[PDB]
Amino acid sequence: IRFERNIVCTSDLDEGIMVVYKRNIVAHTFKVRVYQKVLT
Amino acid sequence: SSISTVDSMIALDIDPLENTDFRVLELYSQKELRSSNVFDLEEIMREFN
């Protein structure tokens, strides 16, 4: 029985810039020309 | 060196909290969500056309 100083205490990640894009859900809208004749 | 020693250190080893990557849980797929309707607008419009 002899104390011998057993205890030996001893002891950002990646900063950066981010840009977040979402998936596009807006439907593509174009212009349709409808030609028709009405016979009454 | 056989007279031995004294382990007076009081252990306080606290394990770190393990990392958790949360899942993006999805209950109903989009197909089921579209198929969960009595009336579908696209079908009605196609039949009218």
Image (cartoon, rainbow, N blue to C red):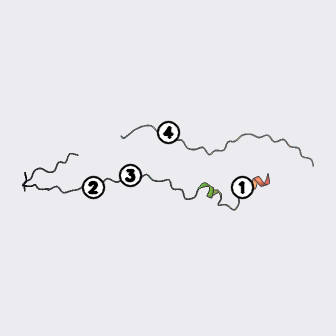
Task: Answer yes or no: are tags 1 and 2 on the same subunit.
Answer: yes
Residue A7 lies, in percent from the top left, at 16, 50
Residue B14 is labelled as 2
Disc 1 marks which amino acid? Answer: Leu
Label 3 and label 4: CA atoms lie apart by 25 Å
Residue under mark 4: which chain is it in?
A
- Residue annotated with mark 3: B19
Q: Is residue A32 above or below residue B36?
A: above
Residue at 62 percent of width and 46 percent of height: A25
- Residue annotated with mark 1: B41
Q: Left or right: where does residue B33 sit relative to residue B39?
A: left
| Residues at circles 1 and 2 in contact by the CB criterion of under 8 Å | no
Label 1 and label 2: CA atoms lie apart by 59 Å
How packed mark 2 is, by other alpha carbons closer than 10 Å (few <14, some 14-19, many 20 or more), is: few
Q: Left or right: where does residue A8 sit relative to residue A22?
A: left
Disc 3 marks which amino acid? Answer: Asn
Residue at 45 percent of width and 53 percent of height: B22
Disc 4 marks which amino acid? Answer: Val
Residue under mark 1: which chain is it in?
B
Task: Answer yes or no: are tags 3 and 4 on the same subunit.
Answer: no
The mark nearer the N terminus, 1 or 3, is: 3
Query: Element at badge 2?
Result: loop
Q: Left or right: where does residue B35 sit relative to residue A5?
A: right
Query: Element at badge 3?
Result: loop
